[PDB]
Amino acid sequence: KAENTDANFYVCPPPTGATVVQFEQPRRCPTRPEGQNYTEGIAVVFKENIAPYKFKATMYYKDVTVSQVWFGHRSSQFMGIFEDRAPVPFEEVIDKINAKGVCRSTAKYVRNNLETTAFHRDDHETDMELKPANAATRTSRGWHTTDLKYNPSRVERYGTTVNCIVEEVDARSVYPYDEFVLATGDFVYMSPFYGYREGSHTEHTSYAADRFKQVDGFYARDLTTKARATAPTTRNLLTTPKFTVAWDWVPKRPSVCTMTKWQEVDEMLRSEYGGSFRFSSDAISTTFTTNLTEYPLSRVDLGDCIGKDARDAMDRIFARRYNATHIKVGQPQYYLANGGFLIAYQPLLSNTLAHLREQSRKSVERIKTTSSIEFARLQFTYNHIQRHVNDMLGRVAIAWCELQNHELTLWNEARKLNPNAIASVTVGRRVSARMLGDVMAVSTCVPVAADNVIVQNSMRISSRPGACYSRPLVSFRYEDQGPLVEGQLGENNELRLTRDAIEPCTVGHRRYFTFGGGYVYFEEYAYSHQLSRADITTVSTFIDLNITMLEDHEFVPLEVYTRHEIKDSGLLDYTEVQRRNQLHDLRFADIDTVIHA
Amino acid sequence: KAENTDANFYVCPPPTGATVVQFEQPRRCPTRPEGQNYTEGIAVVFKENIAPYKFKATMYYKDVTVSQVWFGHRSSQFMGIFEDRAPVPFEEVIDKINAKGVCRSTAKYVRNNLETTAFHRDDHETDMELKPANAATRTSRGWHTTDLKYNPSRVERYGTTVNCIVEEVDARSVYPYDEFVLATGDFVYMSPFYGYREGSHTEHTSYAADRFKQVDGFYARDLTTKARATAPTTRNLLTTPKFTVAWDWVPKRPSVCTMTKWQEVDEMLRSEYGGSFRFSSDAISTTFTTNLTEYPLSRVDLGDCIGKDARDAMDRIFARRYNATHIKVGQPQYYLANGGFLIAYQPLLSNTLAHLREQSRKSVERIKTTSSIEFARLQFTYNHIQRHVNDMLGRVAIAWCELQNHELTLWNEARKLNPNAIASVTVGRRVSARMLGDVMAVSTCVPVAADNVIVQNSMRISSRPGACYSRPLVSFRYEDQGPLVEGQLGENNELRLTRDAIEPCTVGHRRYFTFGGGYVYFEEYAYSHQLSRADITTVSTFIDLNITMLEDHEFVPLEVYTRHEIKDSGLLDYTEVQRRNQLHDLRFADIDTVIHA
Amino acid sequence: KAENTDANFYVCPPPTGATVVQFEQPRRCPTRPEGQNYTEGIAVVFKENIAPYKFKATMYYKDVTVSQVWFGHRSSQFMGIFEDRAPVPFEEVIDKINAKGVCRSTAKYVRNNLETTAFHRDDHETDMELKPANAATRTSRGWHTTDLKYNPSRVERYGTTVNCIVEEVDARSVYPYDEFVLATGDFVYMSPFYGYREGSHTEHTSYAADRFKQVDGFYARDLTTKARATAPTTRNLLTTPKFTVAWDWVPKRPSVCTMTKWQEVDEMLRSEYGGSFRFSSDAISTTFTTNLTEYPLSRVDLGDCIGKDARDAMDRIFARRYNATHIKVGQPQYYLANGGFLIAYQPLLSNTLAHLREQSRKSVERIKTTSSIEFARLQFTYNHIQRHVNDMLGRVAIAWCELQNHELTLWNEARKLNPNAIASVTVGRRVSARMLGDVMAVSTCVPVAADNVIVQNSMRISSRPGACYSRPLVSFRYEDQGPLVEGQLGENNELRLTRDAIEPCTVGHRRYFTFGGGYVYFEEYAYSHQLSRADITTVSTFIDLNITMLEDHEFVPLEVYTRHEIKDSGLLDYTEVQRRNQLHDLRFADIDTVIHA
Ligand SMILES: *[C@@H]1O[C@H](CO)[C@@H](O[C@@H]2O[C@H](CO)[C@@H](O)[C@H](O)[C@H]2NC(C)=O)[C@H](O)[C@H]1NC(C)=O
Ligand SMILES: *[C@@H]1O[C@H](CO)[C@@H](O[C@@H]2O[C@H](CO)[C@@H](O)[C@H](O)[C@H]2NC(C)=O)[C@H](O)[C@H]1NC(C)=O
Ligand SMILES: *[C@@H]1O[C@H](CO)[C@@H](O[C@@H]2O[C@H](CO)[C@@H](O)[C@H](O)[C@H]2NC(C)=O)[C@H](O)[C@H]1NC(C)=O
Ligand SMILES: *[C@@H]1O[C@H](CO)[C@@H](O)[C@H](O)[C@H]1NC(C)=O
Ligand SMILES: *[C@@H]1O[C@H](CO)[C@@H](O)[C@H](O)[C@H]1NC(C)=O
Ligand SMILES: *[C@@H]1O[C@H](CO)[C@@H](O)[C@H](O)[C@H]1NC(C)=O
Ligand SMILES: *[C@@H]1O[C@H](CO)[C@@H](O)[C@H](O)[C@H]1NC(C)=O
Ligand SMILES: *[C@@H]1O[C@H](CO)[C@@H](O)[C@H](O)[C@H]1NC(C)=O
Ligand SMILES: *[C@@H]1O[C@H](CO)[C@@H](O)[C@H](O)[C@H]1NC(C)=O
């Protein structure tokens, strides 16, 4: 009896003609995409120039100090100090300071609608040469005359001081550059590019024309060294109510640029995909997307440095590598990418492939740029990855498809041998199978309880000596009480009624046979025992393939410096001060009490 | 003799019963995961409102200027100018400026604990109408009375000036909004929401109640246009020691919000995975993670705009697309993600699938947000990729497993034909193989030196004319001097002793046979020569599969603007100034010398 | 006739000896890389300390106020208020304020080169105790004496006020820490670490030595609480022209550090690849690249906290997990990664694997750090992904290669059965194939028009009763008028001339046969009809594999806060103010008009 019973039994007769089936034809294997045409080239990326136009100048003024003093016995107290900074008149700058490096001990200027005049020491005007300032770590240059305050003499009236001061400083002007400031925190409400030449008079000024002046062929005389006329300039000279500042007038457009060069890309591969271009600098790990057309520097505001810098850089680069390997291809091309980034691009071709497409590339505004260039480095990554995995996986499907094609060539010859099995496998269920011409006549098989099956001890034929069986005989019943059938066993638990599986008696006749969960054994055509597959050392026909799915992962908010670490980086907080300062009175004083008597 | 000897030889007899082996059964192929259920919906993302509460007001004050002058022959010098900014009294604002647009030529205010009174021109009080300020590019509005300083008349006392000034400015208050400032850099130590209505008196104030006032049904009269009563307001009026500022009192909570709307997401797919939710806006390329529960706006501080804005936006969006395709699903849902981001989410369902889960979603504090939203766009990416590669690779393993299943169906029939080979392959080593029942009796093969093997010139049988051999005869010896065996050759360098491979003599009898590194040839059962595989044009049975592993790549530190490019973007550096300014004295003066006589 | 004609026909004779071919040998399957050796360890990452050295001090000064008043009938006006802040002399700080908490009602100090003396109320010196300031929300502590300004008495001279003020404030010094400032916005041009001990005199000072002092064993007496001598200190005392500030002198190097601890990494796997190291904190999702050598803290400037903090942190961590599982491995190791990031790393080994490599790890400068740590989190990601996909795909190629190896074992036995087909498949074109020894004699097949082919109704043999054909007879012609050949049909549209495919007549003889686009049917060896494959329910032999390529995706510029949202976050804009302020005069005054008479 079927000891090992963790299986099902089947009985498969010759499958009646109907039904008949056919194998699926070879499938059309997919094709590798032609790929993606990339254009090798050099690129330069500009950015919204948030940097203020920087230049240098010179301040000329005098620190006037009028002091009143009250004299008492064995003591003295300041009664009211009046400090002011007054301009050094135009002529006093040209004829006095520049030429000789001197300055009047007197100050004459308009203040509060009147011609006030101050005399140092309250003594007749004496011209006094200038001397370098004192200890000044990390400070631009500066000179002056007076070094001591003047106070009234002993008694029981007033004293005026006049220190002609001149300082070299750093000036900072920002778009639209209609005005600028200094390192002293002093505003100057005139465009640094104001003047007369170049129609500079068009530029902005808040002052009367008589205040401003513009000296031509001006030879500055560097004090201290006393050196002079190193270079002639068109010295602009404005006279503020509090001082007189001057600087070398320079052209606007050439000196400024609303954009700043950010990156020099040696190889910026350019490709089209979806009505846009693709610039991927693998060197920097970045990818930009731009419309198909270019961008005229004409619509740009004061972006003169742009074209200038682009050319210089590119030509510079083309001379390091490409000058031998490749060759230029048309005039510079400019495209604008998302995030407000301007891309200067010059295509390249190696002699190996020795254009018209490059042609036909063609108020005022200004460009804004995103402080974050991550969306691009992201795109870059994704694409380079996606593109890869796709281009790769595709190759698989093809080979696979092709494999299944060749495999069929095998299934064809195979079905000839064991249709009953081959077909059963191709139908995913035990079925009777036989070849009816080129197609296959088939009819399902029938399940049989293993508990109802038992084998005969004899593989021999009492009625036919000399000859024996090739397969031991068996008996079974579908139902729990069903009739008993004299059918012989076939491969893989099939119950072949027709007992025509025979073979002449053989010497040294060992043989194992599939029998339920395990096998059955027979020595010399005589039964032996049943066993489990475990006993028989199993060998595999499969090519192993160990795979592991990519695990998850958490990306936590991570920052190098929180904005608060920045609001603190500022050594001085203008808000902290003014708050505490304008709160000073409230803390240490009462502003509501009135007194009288 | 075996000329081509870059190979090994084997002799395979009928493998003795022991040992016997079995093929590995079909393996259980993995199953596709049910997938990931995504919930379609609309979302809105708020952020820590770092923006200061912005509002407008009006300043009212007078620029008082007392000047002392010393008169000399042919000259005159200011002896001490005293400038001050004094408030314009309450009544003077309501009865004078508002109604008629005028202002007194006199200033009466408390300063340093006393009732000082200033008269413009030192002349009896005259009411003077106000006039718009002068040229003012990029400046809010402003008016005034006086336009010239008043100085003492010729001699050899003092002159007071009074310019009633009023300016429209921009006020800025920040959390907790207990106070605010102006564009003039003037602090006002009172909560902008202070007053009486709405229990505003609860709000913060550093001033006595008599200073502050709150006019009801106030009809402002726009100067210049002289238009008036366009709209009535509850004008708040505070009087600082230096001026009198006023503004329309407004409610707090409605006007402010500690959070600001950042992004309107049309489709924010929501899914659960690992006790958290998944909101992936594929449009923006971002993914947020939130706890399973919601977040009550109750724990929020003054976050009233939140719910308001969320509703407006969502309903707005639902009317563009979803209003036809989908339908709302319950009240708005709010979840908090990592990085301090608040997510407003409203689920959606198309009629095709026409909830309780949405239910059961349920001092004071404030939310902080990370300035970097990259950890999210990272997560988003990773997942969308990982999830893909996994979902894909899985499909492979399955198909593969299935392939190996079907493949077995072939290996079964195949072993019947060339067990000696099929098995040798399944054992990874040359072995003798024969079918013992359903299993396979096997016994390893034996290596034989090729240098010891030589073939016989004759494939014919001198003793048996008419008939010949199907395989030429050979001889060999295992050892270097071992006995010589009369065995015939079998397929693939097997040495079948039993010389029973025969065939009747055939006409036009060409035949090639595997012979060491190459082959051996025989014409008409008579030897010819040996050759190498090279000669025979080889054909492949393999389906090619060209693969390439993803190359490495370097991600270099890349920034659009270094923090230093920012510390410079600021036109004015409060630190640069105050340093140079407070260093001014050290550079151009001595503070250690004392004088007397 | 061939009704279904969407196919081609072929005639295949026994392929003449030439030409002959051979199958491709098994290919050498690739090997799994040994992998990547990772070193488990703990790490700590420092960063460019952009934070200013923070410490506390105390200001001591007096608010002197000299006021002149003009008296008139029924009125009075300030004629000129002179406000000044003067220092509280050294002795007055030690003997008066510290001990008793009092201060002189008089101020004696040098101003404008003279010994001015101020008396509160202009009355003989009286010592006045100090009292806490008034209402002060979010302000450090502060005390004072006077609380009211002093003004001249009724008439028709001057009044001086003296408010001894002392404030606790927050001091801020930045590299090189040669000077510092206060919360009052007051600069102090002396290195906070100046003094005498520790050779502090080396530090920077802009003042004469007599101004600065350094009290030893100083016991501060906390006012209000009047508590004293809680702790003795080396009180530094500098006396600026405007005040006298003091603070506890402390060592420099220990108190400061040009680097700040950023992240404590529990597990920072370290590995080598391409002459550099690999530190991947999977916890944070980050990867750093450093040279093979270390970095001496010797080249570091004032980076003392570094080693200190590194040790504390690490040892701390090693006591939470590793103390039991792993064991320390040598002294701390420091490497510098790109982006200016310093990595403190301590390797680890579990007892399971229980070093020399760790050894041999070995003016002044300072480190700069990138504000963006994304290039790293990028690298991290890419690698972890790339490495995965590679390590995975590889496994495929191998298994695949191996599969094709085993597959051959099948192709060998298969070709024996249907060479004509097997070979045709291996040649990618219909060819005649037969086994010539071990190789295969082959010769291409010939295409034949289907329109020229017709089958015979009889599968029977009139001349040979009892026996019949196994394959119906056919006729055809290559050319459009070519000769008619008596060849029988073979499998797959082959035209086997030799009509030797026979079989005895059979009962119930159904049979289908491939016939052009469809099939042909015969009942009892008598023709029936033709049909299309559609009729016959097709069954597949292929293992399906549904794949999908990863779709594209757009990464749009996305920012949490634009830099402009930051330029606004600042409650006060020093530029806005000074612009409007220094523009005040232009708006409400004329600076070009002169008057006289
Ligand atoms: C780059 O890819 C394009 C896109 O396919 C290729 O253009 C194809 O070229 C082949 C012939 O070489 C043909 O299919 C057509 O001429 C093109 N088809 C398409 C779809 O465009 C191109 O050949 C590739 N490489 C280069 C250098 O041109
Ligand atoms: C979404 O995925 C879940 C997770 O499997 C699915 O829920 C399963 O549904 C199937 C029957 O359709 C069964 O396995 C169980 O009902 C669920 N199993 C698990 C593991 O949850 C769900 O069907 C999927 N789709 C939808 C729209 O529900
Ligand atoms: C980590 O990977 C390296 C690199 O291969 C391994 O070193 C190899 O070890 C095997 C023997 O185990 C041999 O190929 C050589 O000794 C090494 N080859 C190379 C290329 O280096 C190492 O074994 C791996 N793991 C450990 C823990 O050592
Ligand atoms: C590019 O052109 C398209 C129209 O083709 C326009 O919609 C889009 O705004 C342009 N992009 C930029 C960056 O200006
Ligand atoms: C082209 O390349 C070479 C590389 O050595 C470079 O030195 C040179 O400047 C370039 N061309 C010439 C001849 O200048
Ligand atoms: C979410 O809830 C968990 C507990 O379930 C808590 O540990 C965690 O802090 C919460 N996250 C946020 C963002 O508050
Ligand atoms: C629904 O969608 C349509 C789209 O045309 C939109 O115009 C409409 O406002 C929505 N519903 C209605 C009827 O308002
Ligand atoms: C690391 O060392 C290499 C030379 O081996 C040098 O070129 C490079 O500048 C160094 N990197 C850093 C971060 O200093
Ligand atoms: C080692 O690990 C344990 C974990 O419980 C920790 O508590 C302990 O501090 C460590 N070692 C010891 C004994 O302190």
Image: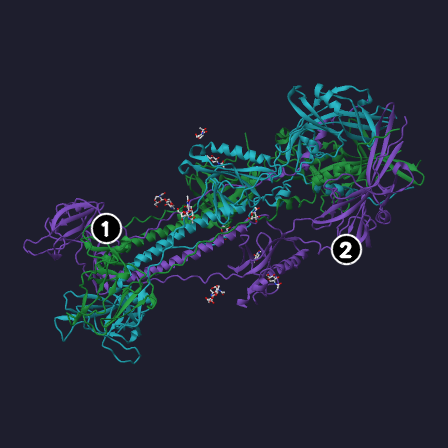
Chain colours: A cyan, B purple, C green
Direction from residue B31 to residue C20 in the image, left or right: left
Looking at mark 1, is its residue's CB closer than 8 Å to ligand 1? no
Whether callout 1 and callout 2 share a subunit is answered no
Q: Which quarter of the frame holds ligand 7? A: bottom right
C595 vs C143, nearest the viewer? C595
Question: At which x and y percent is residue A485?
Answer: 24, 78
Q: Which residue is mark 1?
A: C22
Q: Which residue is mark 2?
A: B200
Q: Residue furthest left?
A: B463
A87 vs C593, nearest the viewer? C593
Please identify the quarter of the rendering in which residue A74 is found: top right
Direction from residue A214 to residue A535 in the image, left or right: left
Please identify the quarter of the rendering in which residue A448 is found: bottom left
The residue at 14%/65% (across/down) is A507
Q: CA distance from mark 1 to mark 2?
A: 100 Å
Split into 4 quadrants, where in the image is the N terminus of chain C?
Answer: bottom left
Question: At which x and y percent is residue C364?
Answer: 55, 31
Report the amino acid beneath label 2: Ser
Question: At which x and y percent is residue A441?
Answer: 28, 70
Label 1 marks a residue whose chain is: C
Q: How many marks?
A: 2
Name the mark on residue A129. none
Asked which secondary structure carries label 1, the reply is: strand
Direction from residue A167 to residue B533 in the image, left or right: left
Direction from residue B1 to residue C389 in the image, left or right: right
When the figure is inspected, residue A449 is found, relative to residue B273, above or below; the finding is below
